[PDB]
Image 1 (cartoon, rainbow, N blue to C red):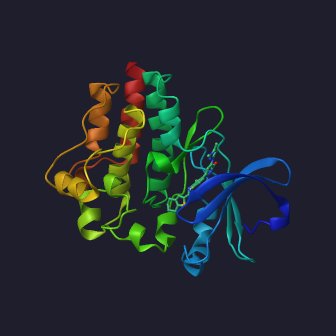
Image 2: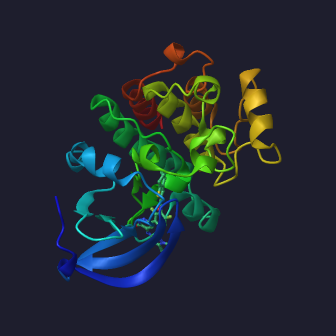
Image 3: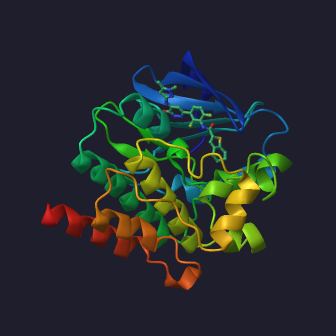
Length: 264
Ligand SMILES: Cc1cc(Nc2cc(-c3ccc(F)c(NC(=O)c4cc5c(s4)CCCC5)c3F)n[nH]c2=O)nn1C
């Protein structure tokens, strides 16, 4: 879906990410959208447009909805569903004292449902983390920017020893061999659950990225946050098996989460 740029009205700046400036605006005067304006040289653009069709076809309530792209001018635009409460990490930190435990579990469920959908389509996120989830005006969490890490042109982000690589969300086989799979998204999801239940703390705080890699390679795992029950911690901890094939699927994780809800 090629969006006509004449149908976009820019309204507000939303900050800057791995591809440069992001704006809030409207599509056809009515629908609230976010618009990434892709900084030249920041993205493998031919590669992105080449593979853009499969992303058009991903649709789930808990996935941020793609509206489309503008590719007939530079900078390229990516147009998505606007999420008025912004990214999940800042939302957790700003509302930290208000959350009930049942709401923390519901946020995890939202993300798990989106990821079970992506898993069913054999589509990898590759940078799942609370910073890449968004929150709407009703508090629903949705997964954002799935698959886009593949198109980043920035050695600090693409190298496992780069300053911007998501080391703290990565399993050993990604840090050692760059072996991304559904099971590396599973690992990241466990870290995301930890971010939720810690109310937005930084994983492995005071460890450097390389110290993090060393310690998880040797079996260290994130501690149980105060607000996580044992049953909840067992779920997130299952995401962190050293061996990828021992980690659950998102279907199983979703069933575990629903089971905890039912018990509650
Ligand atoms: C109050 C409020 C609402 C609101 N709502 C939104 C903000 C954004 C948004 C803004 C800046 C960003 F930097 C990003 N992330 C990125 O650009 C990238 C992430 C990744 C990229 S690029 C390539 C590698 C993989 C990860 C955003 F997603 N989008 N959509 C929204 O709805 N924001 N605020 C402040």
